[PDB]
Length: 199
Ligand SMILES: [Cl-]
Image (cartoon, rainbow, N blue to C red; front, side, top):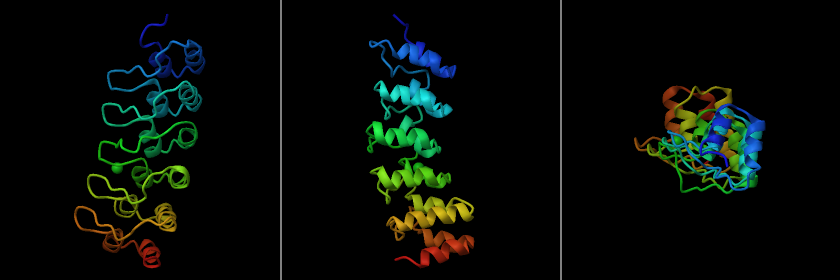
């Protein structure tokens, strides 16, 4: 007999026990939305409330329901380094790979750009994500990891991980540039050396 919004309010309040209380109601529609198009699951993913997120996924919450800026719980978890939640999603739900973020990207591109190497590994191992996918700018995960970032150890490691998993480094973005082009222009010596070792 809960009113619409009860579960959103419990998620906003980070109230794990209240969430579980509500979910005991078998009639409850778990994917109600707020003014920004967020479901309780999306709120939990933003907050990194892992137990709440697991509870909602077990009750059938849609990991692919996008909010007003095109972020679904899945896309956001991948992009923003919510590793535990992402691992759970990859085991207990089915990602929709025809849904993209506001820039036309997937979960893997932003995970790499943002340095979330554990998320990258997860998506490469059991994600289905195309390593060569491109966003609206023509950027791949490799290009973003090289060209948009600082070229440091973390990004060197992300570049190596991608190449070891068969990333195509010959892909050009919308400006006609490859990952090798960016590393060279920016003076990212260690990345250039890594890239030179692969075809
Ligand atoms: Cl993207």
